[PDB]
Image (cartoon, helix red, strand yellow):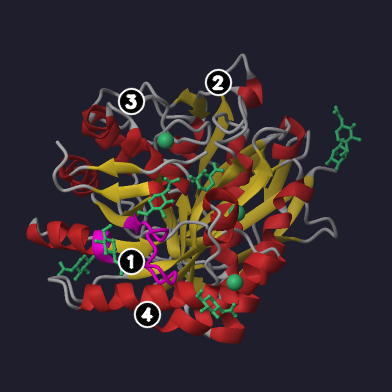
Amino acid sequence: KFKNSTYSRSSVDVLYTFANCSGLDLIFGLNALLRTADLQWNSSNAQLLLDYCSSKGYNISWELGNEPNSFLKKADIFINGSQLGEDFIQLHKLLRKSTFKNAKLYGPDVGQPRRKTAKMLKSFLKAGGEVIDSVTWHHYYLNGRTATREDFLNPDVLDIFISSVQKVFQVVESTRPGKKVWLGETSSAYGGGAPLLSDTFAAGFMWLDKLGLSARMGIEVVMRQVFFGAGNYHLVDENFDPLPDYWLSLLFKKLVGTKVLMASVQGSKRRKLRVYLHCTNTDNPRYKEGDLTLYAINLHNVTKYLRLPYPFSNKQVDKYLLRPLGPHGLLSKSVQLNGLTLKMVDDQTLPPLMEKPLRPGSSLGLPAFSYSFFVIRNAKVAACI
Amino acid sequence: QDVVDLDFFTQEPLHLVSPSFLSVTIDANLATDPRFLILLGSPKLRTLARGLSPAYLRFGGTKTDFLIFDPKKE
Ligand SMILES: *[C@@H]1O[C@H](CO[C@@H]2O[C@@H](C)[C@@H](O)[C@@H](O)[C@@H]2O)[C@@H](O)[C@H](O)[C@H]1NC(C)=O
Ligand SMILES: *[C@@H]1O[C@H](CO)[C@@H](O)[C@H](O)[C@H]1NC(C)=O
Ligand SMILES: *[C@@H]1O[C@H](CO)[C@@H](O)[C@H](O)[C@H]1NC(C)=O
Ligand SMILES: *[C@@H]1O[C@H](CO)[C@@H](O)[C@H](O)[C@H]1NC(C)=O
Ligand SMILES: *[C@@H]1O[C@H](CO)[C@@H](O)[C@H](O)[C@H]1NC(C)=O
Ligand SMILES: O=C(O)[C@H]1CNCC(O)(O)[C@H]1O
Ligand SMILES: [Cl-]
Ligand SMILES: [Cl-]
Ligand SMILES: [Cl-]
């Protein structure tokens, strides 16, 4: 199905300019399917690109291959994990001889850990683990072709992610203990997303739960498929309009800090009410060192009222509740924050993200099929200072 | 009854995520779009991308392994 294409210096400059102008750090995936007679990686094309990027002073991070578990199906070429590790060693030597000698290298961008993908990841980390800065793997919950609305709302579907994460760490801890683990490419549903689902408010349950579980379980970076593009799972549509998952991602960015804590619900069922707890993002100008950010998903069909434990039970709390703009409910492409539709001010201006101050000591209201952030002001948590 | 008590563990950080914890991709297949320069040059799109800084932007996808650098091409 997939044919070779070429790309130009112009295309590399379009990509870098976009990243540089947007304050993003570019990671560029190199072609792993360029192979010598005896099925070693042929590095000559990568050398041409490395030399061009060095010549323009482009600070770029590297990957080599995408889903190498799939090469036999996609390209009728099998590369084992041992060989792929050797290929990474050869790329690492090229980076060390380039103008950016400390450039980062990530891999191997394997699919989620089935028997044969786990085997490839294990043989890859044995062989090439020393030269990668982080281990990358990919995750999707469902086939976008067959995914249902019910699937997007089902805690039994959300929970499958936990076993994938546990299996990747089991491989990494048996081969390269302590190596950082990244989700290199992830979203709701593969094959470009679930039509009329992956681009809606309903998509946000999987996205926010995945962020929560990833942070809680030790994943250091989660890369969302895709910021912009042909797939339904895009954060920004073809008209450059932000979808609900964009707004959810912007709020997460503004409110949720680097230090991960834990929240849990005291009842025996820990299924439809999902709660996560970090220190507040120190860069949010509204908040101060020691503040907490709670985020919660309610997959019940009724409102739940959350009570904060001592010593947080009487603190001022800032609510950031997301609900769809009607009439399409969870299948809406528009979202409201505390009842205000989120929309660009103009092409250059994001809107302000207006909190709703709750009366101190009130229970936190979480409507049916909704998600919210709650900042606990003056929490004075020592772990967060 | 629809009231739920939360329990919080706050003693110490259980993990530290990157400041770029929430990162994004661009599919390598987008570079095969004739309008690639228009799309990524969009001032509207760059404003939206700046809102998620700091973050990684990973350029990759199935097409990663079907793309060849041609330094002659225009
Ligand atoms: C709502 O979901 C019900 C099962 O969930 C439980 O009952 C409801 C009323 C909530 O209190 C929730 O917290 C419980 O977990 C279903 O049996 C019922 O079919 C659904 N009701 C409606 C209106 O769709
Ligand atoms: C792409 O080119 C590589 C070598 O440069 C080759 O191995 C592969 O068969 C080509 N793929 C297709 C489907 O043309
Ligand atoms: C690698 O590919 C380049 C360009 O296609 C070719 O000139 C070179 O001979 C190849 N190297 C090996 C070892 O096959
Ligand atoms: C490249 O950028 C990283 C931040 O992503 C920076 O820490 C590193 O030192 C940079 N390398 C150079 C030489 O600019
Ligand atoms: C992995 O593939 C390489 C390259 O073809 C081969 O030389 C090696 O024997 C293979 N290892 C295993 C265990 O299959
Ligand atoms: O939507 C999908 O199925 C993705 C799977 N991984 C590679 C890719 O990002 O290019 C997509 O094809
Ligand atoms: Cl996968
Ligand atoms: Cl293998
Ligand atoms: Cl795309």
Q: Do we see residue A257 in this rendering?
A: yes
Reply yes or no: does residue A37 show up in magenta: yes
Q: Position of residue A152 (x, y in %)?
A: 69, 38
The amino acid at mark 1 is Asn
Q: Amino acid at mark 3?
A: Met
For label 1, the residue is A42
Give the residue at mark 3.
A344
Distance of label 3 from label 1 (alpha carbons): 46 Å
Q: Position of residue B41 (x, y in %)?
A: 21, 32
Q: Which residue does the image show at 34% across and 35% down from the upper left? A: B32
Q: Residue at x 30, y 70 (%)?
A: A104
Q: Earlier in the sequence, mark 1 or mark 2?
A: 1
Q: Nearer the viewer, residue A224 or A6?
A: A6
Residue A116 shown in magenta: no
Q: Nearer the viewer, residue A201 or A104?
A: A104
4 or 2: tag closer to the N-terminus = 4
Q: Marks 4 and 2: which is nearer the front?
A: 4
| Label 4 crowd bin: few (<14), some (14–19), many (20+), radius 10 Å | many
Determine whether A42 is above or below A190 in the image. Answer: below
Label 3 marks which chain's residue? A
Does the closest atom of ligand 3 sit within 8 Å of the Cβ of label 1?
yes
